[PDB]
RNA sequence: GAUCUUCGGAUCACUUUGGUCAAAUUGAAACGAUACAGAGAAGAUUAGCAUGGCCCCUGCACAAGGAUGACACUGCGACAUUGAGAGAAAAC
């Protein structure tokens, strides 16, 4: 019954190159291509952040709108705007 | 707010938001490699052009190529049974 707090103060930026020798970025399909297919179920890297309702939930600007949706990023816990 | 008007007001303008979709593991494709076989015509080597379509790829193309591009190329019962004999059964 208190305003919602922001979880991640920073913005996770995108910079990563798999398999340094044998990968090249693909402009059309925005993903790295070439190199070993690699296990389909291998990339899974444990998530870094985690959330619970108790310490995180609260009011936000979307509570006013009757048809508002939930944060894709609150559940995964990197909503970096808070109550805004 | 600007213009007049006579301090009543009149003019002038008047409803945005191109949305494969919210900051990239879990809704834009198609696969590397290793291991197996491993190149059409009845001996052997080998030119090709076709036929068929829920197979495509390269191409601007209704040219032409990709192993003659590849796969496929088979096969069965609107047979009426009587022709006869034998042992049985039921029957000339
Ligand atoms: K040939
Ligand atoms: Mg041809
Ligand atoms: Mg052919």
Image (spheres, coloured by chain):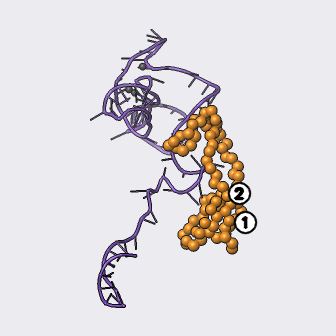
In the picture, measured across the screen, residue A18 lies left or right of residue A65, that is: right
Crowd rating for badge 1 (residues with CA inside 10 Å; few <14, some 14–19, many 20+): few
> In the rendered image, what is the letter of the chain coloured purple?
B
Q: Tell me the residue that label 2 is attached to.
A: A50
Tell me if the residue at label 1 has its CB under 8 Å from ligand 3: no
**Number of numbered discs:** 2
- Residue B88 horizontal/vertical position (percent): 56, 39
Q: Chain of mark 2?
A: A
Q: Is residue B30 above or below residue A62?
A: above
Quadrant location, ligand no. 2: top left
- Is residue A73 in sight in this rendering? yes
- Residue B24 horizontal/vertical position (percent): 60, 50
Q: Tell me the residue that label 1 is attached to.
A: A55
Q: Quick one: SS at disc 1?
A: helix
Q: Quadrant of the C terminus of chain A?
A: bottom right
Q: Earlier in the sequence, mark 2 or mark 1?
A: 2
In the picture, measured across the screen, residue B60 lies left or right of residue A83, that is: left
Asked if the residue under mark 1 is in contact with the one under mark 2, i.e. CB atoms within 8 Å, the reply is: no
Residue placed most toward the observer, B54 or A41: A41
- Residue B91 horizontal/vertical position (percent): 46, 43
The residue depicted at 56 percent of the width and 68 percent of the height is A68
- Is residue A76 in sight in this rendering? no
Residue placed most toward the observer, A35 or B44: A35
Q: Is residue B47 above or below residue A11?
A: above
Q: Quick one: SS at disc 2?
A: loop
> In the rendered image, what is the letter of the chain coloured orange?
A
Report which quarter residue B18 is drawn in: bottom left
Report which quarter residue A74 is drawn in: bottom right
Disc 2 from disc 1: Cα separation: 11 Å
Tell me if the residue at label 2 has its CB under 8 Å from ligand 3: no
């Amino acid at each position: 019954k208190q305003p919602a707090r922001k979880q991640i103060e920073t913005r996770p930026e995108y910079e990563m190159e798999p398999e340094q020798p044998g990968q090249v970025y693909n402009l059309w399909y925005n993903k790295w291509s070439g190199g070993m297919r690699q296990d389909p179920l291998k990339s899974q890297v444990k998530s870094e952040t985690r959330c619970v309702i108790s310490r995180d939930s609260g009011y936000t600007k979307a509570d006013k709108n009757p048809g508002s949706f939930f944060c894709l990023y609150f559940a995964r816990g990197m909503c970096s705007e808070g109550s805004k």
